[PDB]
Amino acid sequence: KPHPWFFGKIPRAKAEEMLSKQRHDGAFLIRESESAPGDFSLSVKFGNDVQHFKVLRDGAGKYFLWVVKFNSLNELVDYHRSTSVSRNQQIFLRDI
Ligand SMILES: NC(=O)CC1NC(=O)C2(CCCCC2)NC(=O)[C@@H](CC(=O)O)[C@@H](c2ccc(C(C(=O)O)C(=O)O)cc2)/C=C/C[C@@H](Cc2cccc3ccccc23)CNC1=O
Ligand SMILES: NC(=O)C[C@@H]1NC(=O)C2(CCCCC2)NC(=O)[C@H](CC(=O)O)[C@@H](c2ccc(C(C(=O)O)C(=O)O)cc2)/C=C/C[C@@H](Cc2cccc3ccccc23)CNC1=O
Ligand SMILES: NC(=O)C[C@H]1NC(=O)C2(CCCCC2)NC(=O)[C@H](CC(=O)O)[C@@H](c2ccc(C(C(=O)O)C(=O)O)cc2)/C=C/C[C@@H](Cc2cccc3ccccc23)CNC1=O
Ligand SMILES: NC(=O)C[C@H]1NC(=O)C2(CCCCC2)NC(=O)[C@H](CC(=O)O)[C@@H](c2ccc(C(C(=O)O)C(=O)O)cc2)/C=C/C[C@@H](Cc2cccc3ccccc23)CNC1=O
Ligand SMILES: NC(=O)C[C@H]1NC(=O)C2(CCCCC2)NC(=O)[C@H](CC(=O)O)[C@@H](c2ccc(C(C(=O)O)C(=O)O)cc2)/C=C/C[C@@H](Cc2cccc3ccccc23)CNC1=O
């Protein structure tokens, strides 16, 4: 499990300066959080800036960027038109 995407204590500013010069949107790194001891931040090139996400943890110690839950069945459906419903195959929802 190589982690060439991990850049340790790279400051937020330097991560932005590095990601700015990348050719593709989605170019990214993970780095230690600026403020939170033991936490990680994900930095991603998107168009003409760089977005930062906190790498969230739950009580079981799992890692995630947002909790994927929906307010309506329709919302669930709309999501899985473009994100697979299967955990092992590529299967998108399509109108019957
Ligand atoms: N990186 C991956 O894609 C790995 C797996 N994850 C999935 O397919 C995923 C994530 C991507 C989108 C589809 C759903 N998620 C899951 O399957 C899930 C569960 C699910 O139903 O979606 C993942 C999981 C279970 C429980 C928690 C929970 C907790 O630990 O208390 C919590 O809230 O923190 C969290 C996550 C189960 C893994 C068991 C896995 C089976 C398993 C593997 C190795 C060891 C054990 C040991 C015990 C039980 C099961 C396993 C199935 N899941 C995967 O292999
Ligand atoms: N996984 C995610 O980041 C999803 C969220 N983020 C967003 O909605 C985003 C998604 C990218 C586009 C802008 C909006 N990002 C942000 O809002 C932000 C905004 C930003 O970039 O300033 C994201 C963030 C804050 C600060 C850092 C910082 C550090 O960790 O000390 C660093 O650069 O190392 C990094 C990231 C804030 C999270 C606060 C979050 C609250 C929070 C959660 C857990 C621990 C702490 C701890 C302290 C403060 C807040 C939190 C709310 N935001 C989100 O959950
Ligand atoms: N959650 C995961 O599955 C990630 C890792 N775990 C493993 O592959 C596993 C997990 C179960 C089977 C044995 C090997 N574990 C390990 O490799 C290891 C260690 C090992 O040989 O078991 C994992 C580790 C280090 C130290 C502790 C712990 C203790 O020693 O009691 C403590 O509190 O210090 C616990 C775990 C090292 C991680 C660094 C990793 C390298 C690393 C170092 C520093 C920063 C980063 C940042 C991002 C990714 C990886 C790293 C190697 N380990 C992994 O990638
Ligand atoms: N719990 C502790 O306080 C002692 C450990 N942790 C630290 O000192 C810490 C404590 C908070 C602030 C930064 C320094 N944390 C860390 O070092 C780190 C990473 C860091 O720089 O923040 C800890 C770590 C690695 C990877 C993950 C990873 C995963 O499990 O997938 C993830 O986040 O998803 C998570 C944590 C690395 C352990 C390797 C350890 C070295 C190591 C041991 C055994 C096998 C391998 C194998 C490969 C690389 C490193 C190691 C170093 N860390 C520690 O022993
Ligand atoms: N993780 C916890 O919160 C505590 C668990 N305690 C245990 O007894 C354990 C402690 C380690 C030694 C074996 C048994 N853990 C487990 O049962 C399992 C580990 C195990 O070997 O059975 C634990 C677990 C699941 C999946 C993974 C997986 C992943 O997330 O990708 C992976 O290995 O990569 C890792 C760990 C969680 C299961 C769901 C838990 C139930 C659950 C909650 C929320 C959503 C789902 C969704 C699907 C299935 C189960 C759940 C039952 N397990 C536990 O409560």
Image (cartoon, rainbow, N blue to C red):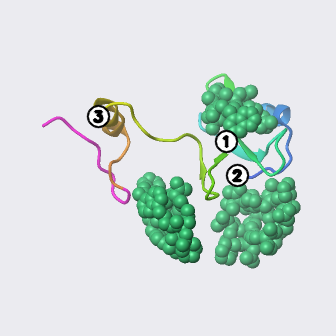
Q: Ligand 3 near label 2 (Cβ, under 8 Å)?
A: no
Task: For label 2, count other residues whose C-alpha is less than 10 Å away and answer few (under 14), some (14-19) or many (20+).
Answer: few
Bounds of the magenta segment: 87-96
Q: Is residue 95 magenta?
A: yes
Query: Main SS type for the magenta part?
Result: loop
Amino acid tagged 2: Trp
Give the CA distance from mark 1 to mark 3. 33 Å
Q: Nearer the viewer, mark 2 or mark 3?
A: 3
Instruction: Say if 86 sits above or below 27 in the image.
Output: below
Residue at 74 percent of width and 52 percent of height: 6
Marks 1 and 2, the one that precedes in the sequence: 2
Circle 2 sits in a helix, a strand or a loop, which is it? loop
Any part of residue 52 in sight: no
Which residue position is annotated with label 2? 5
Instruction: Say if 14 sits above or below 32 in the image.
Output: above
Amino acid tagged 3: Leu
Q: Nearer the viewer, mark 1 or mark 3?
A: 3
Residue at 21 percent of width and 38 percent of height: 94
Which residue position is annotated with label 3? 73
Evaluate if marks 1 and 2 touch, with contact meaning CB atoms under 8 Å apart: yes
Evaluate if marks 2 and 3 touch, with contact meaning CB atoms under 8 Å apart: no
